[PDB]
Length: 88
Length: 153
Length: 177
RNA sequence: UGAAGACAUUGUCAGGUGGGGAGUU
Image 1: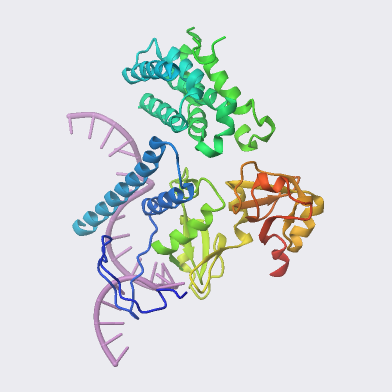
Image 2: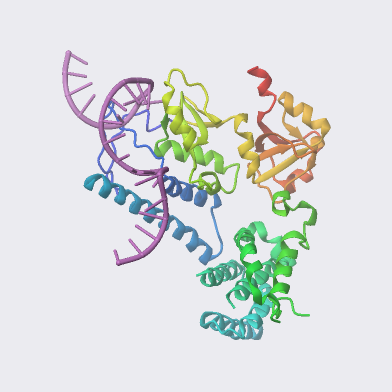
């Protein structure tokens, strides 16, 4: 058993998009996360994974919904940052 | 089978009153929900707490009594022995109601209608409802000497 | 000093979620319009206020040594490890708690796993391998670890049976003295 | 036309830092 990271295994296009890939052995630019909104999105996923299985259908929906609102706020915040930087 | 049929009709009426928000019936409905929640399926028990939270959030958007009525019901739901033993399994956390009761204490002081007034939920005085919530948080029937000291303070 | 990337923040919070409940409270805004952030300085993660972080930028990176509270370090293989320097954070919002008696506090501070004879108070409905914070009878946090058995299964265990695996103890402060 | 208020905001020099952005060997 050996890690796929250790082997130089090409990345494959699937239902999950590969996106823009980065060359190996080069500067993969650090994308810092420091906003409260960006931290909230990551935190919601972590909490959802730890909680795991919930028997209630409504309680399961609410856990998914709070991640959706966290994503929406982060996207709105980053959009406003782009507009301010582009305009001013 | 007949119990299931009656439970279907009894609970359907309870929820349709909650959706339409009849002011003179919500106290009676919440007593029924607290009385008969342990007779229904487990997965619906967590839904009842979530439905209570939406009612409180709607009133957060008279109004003081309705939010206190739901908070009394939520604690009375968990004070049952069956629901208490299923706390961990069914993910029944009352942290939302404890926090909401905490942020409302300052506003309730300024309210002048606190005194304009065998039941456990349907009580005519908002001050009485406040005392029932406070007794649940600070003097629970179960685990009375394991309560977090910070919450008490 | 630089803030965390999105991969690193996920790793740090995953380890913290193993031990604490309300991680939203960690990064929630304060009264004076300030908040706590995460910073990396020589593969060590630091929990510190944003105002302190901004005014600590004047110090050159080769001249900075500590900042706020140190949660732990990222290992060479990319794996976050908590340190006892993070215990005050862990105890504030601990999910599962274990209390050890006087006969178990001293062995724990020397670096031994808790056994049944040491436990004086459990936390009911605690799964097998969960993160717990260890206290003594005076509610003084001694450290943290991972539980060996479930609470129900630990009750029927032998007195000389491991109930918690040690991961950090306050005696490590004597190490770096 | 009303409100706040000589405080903010903003601007100019001198610095500290800069694992981020641009360029060069």
